[PDB]
Amino acid sequence: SKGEELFTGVVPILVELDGDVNGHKFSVSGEGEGDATYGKLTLKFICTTGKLPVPWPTLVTTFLQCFARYPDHMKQHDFFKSAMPEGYVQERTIFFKDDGNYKTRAEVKFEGDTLVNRIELKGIDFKEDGNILGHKLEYNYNSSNVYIMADKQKNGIKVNFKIRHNIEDGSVQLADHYQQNTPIGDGPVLLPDNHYLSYQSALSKDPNEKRDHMVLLEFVTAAGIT
């Protein structure tokens, strides 16, 4: 079985990120599970290399759009599942307004019965005491919309959206995200009509975990096509 069928149940997820932000190197491991039928992800991330040198909320968007719930009438527009199990490559630049930038490359594919997202992230030109390195961002998340359109020129899609990280003084740190996805395997794939994914998310902590970590729950629904 392969394609829009592998996500009918709960699917285990793995995340591996090796990072370098302004020369500060770190690694994060995550695990949990997803159920695309309900548009639900549940993940816990632990920084295995010590103190995370950037705020957890700045990595939420980095840490599985294949688990979006697409309505039946939108089900023929779900690129992410249509590319599975071969998977896709995910690339981003994330521009933090008046601060540094992130660049990410990720691989999403089925390894056995587990979906695995392996990510590399490098960040540069961040201020030593900016909102990111100075840990001035509130630990919370707002509701966002993620806009998707086809990029036929690359046999993939182009995606962009803008996240708004709340700062402890009531101001906002903006993060302009630009992303494109192309399949990892060589083959057909579904290219969508213009549409968006509606995101809601929640961050918490595990009271019994001694290490720096993040527990994350996401709800994802496709919309924008009538």
Image (cartoon, rainbow, N blue to C red):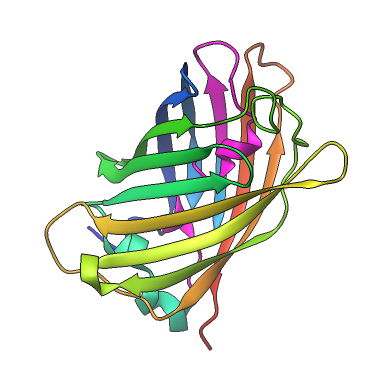
Residue depicted at 41% across the width and 73% down the height: 149
Which quarter of the image is occupied by the N terminus? bottom left
Residue depicted at 60% across the width and 38% down the height: 99
199 vs 109, left or right, is: right
Q: Is residue 67 above or below residue 27?
A: below
- Seen from the viewer's position, the closer of residues 162 and 192 is 162
Residue depicted at 26% across the width and 60% down the height: 83
The x, y position of residue 53, in whole percent, is: 58, 20
- Seen from the viewer's position, the closer of residues 1 and 161 is 161
- Seen from the viewer's position, the closer of residues 32 and 26 is 26
Whether residue 40 can be seen here: yes
The x, y position of residue 49, in whole percent, is: 50, 12
Residue sitting at the far left: 186
The x, y position of residue 107, in whole percent, is: 30, 42
Residue sitting at the far right: 169
Res 224 quadrant in image: bottom right
Q: Is residue 35 above or below residue 189?
A: above
Q: Is residue 132 above or below residue 60?
A: above
| Residue 68 highlighted magenta (yes or no) | yes
135 vs 114, left or right, is: right
Residue depicted at 35% across the width and 78% down the height: 76
The x, y position of residue 130, in whole percent, is: 69, 30
Find the magenta span and give its range: 43-70
Res 159 quadrant in image: bottom left
Res 145 quadrant in image: bottom right
| Residue 60 highlighted magenta (yes or no) | yes
Q: Is residue 99 above or below residue 220?
A: above
Whether residue 4 can be seen here: no
Residue sitting at the far bottom: 226
